[PDB]
Length: 221
Length: 218
Length: 8
Ligand SMILES: C[C@]12CC[C@@H]3c4ccc(O)cc4CC[C@H]3[C@@H]1CC[C@@H]2O
Ligand SMILES: C[C@]12CC[C@@H]3c4ccc(O)cc4CC[C@H]3[C@@H]1CC[C@@H]2O
Image (cartoon, rainbow over all chains, first blue to last red; front, side, top):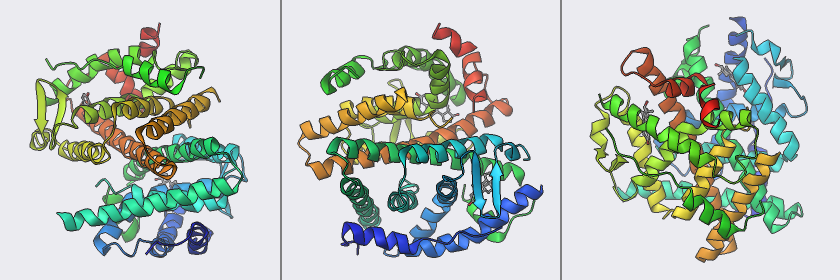
């Protein structure tokens, strides 16, 4: 399906982008927001090139595995313009000290990641690539028939990688700088995984009431 | 950073920690990991740029990455043993021996799946020591000089693939695939850390003071 | 402090 050009892939992800939603009691605000973002994420994943080519069983597995990572990289992205603060919503800009209300360790890492994106001057075209990478890669390591689909995910991942390199090449970066920047971005995904696992364990230890969908995404971990 | 790509590889290969033997399943694994940590500390000191960092940063990096390093080492040792995890030459565990400990078999499955991934990618020893050094340096950043060393290992990885005969497109594609595995290695570590802390709170096995401190940092 | 001492 993905025999799209590099910029065809970019504009496909850009158009598939979900909107920025508005929003003890702190846990209620964050979990209700995440719940409403989950629905938009599901339909976003469907518009990711090569995702609907997978079986429903495998689409579920990938979403259950990466949902908090996807929420976190989204948060970190829209928080770049607000140093030392996390923009969960336009009407919910939270500072570090407000993390002590529940979690401040999780806030710190999210803030450090948002700062890291600023120092790299992360572009929107690169962001949508990274988020689609997370979706497809986070759960890939978890018969020939089942082999060919893992191979499919691998091919799409290579495609998005080509797209990231294309963006850096277009940006006028030298060949060496492309390799280094690509490496830096993908290494940040490791930290995003780290924050996800920590946030997941936190959400579980907090188990304010949660919705059916959110309980299910949590129960997967 | 004043090292060539070949000097970087050779230094990392030469700094490789020894394969230890095992001396209550959790007891054997705990005892092994504890003795390995000591050899990991000396290994880290031989990683180009690590001793240049402040001692506080050296502590923080090892505290955050110690389980990742043990796991990727384990995964590397088990590459020639499909369906098995070689914790030690005298401790070759099949998948089903993970059932011996509560919530251990799903950790094994991820470790076994990682080994098969390295196997399918035909991971080389030169690439392995690079990946392990990257883990040590990157896994504690988001908690200047570090990033310039990380860019050096990136250049080294590319040099290897270019020397291995991979086209320019295959290089950054394989580079991406290798680094995306570190995300899964990160995932396994966090799950292993939660499991290890679970065993400590249930008094399943006694932990050395070194390991206690490793858990406390998480 | 523990680890702090094997890097002496
Ligand atoms: C999952 C938590 C509540 C929901 C939070 C959220 C909610 C919405 C969102 O877009 C991103 C995040 C990331 C941090 C999450 C929190 C980390 C711990 C807490 O349980
Ligand atoms: C840390 C655990 C015990 C020690 C195990 C070990 C022990 C030695 C080693 O070289 C690698 C690993 C990785 C898996 C580890 C286990 C995962 C969960 C368990 O707590």
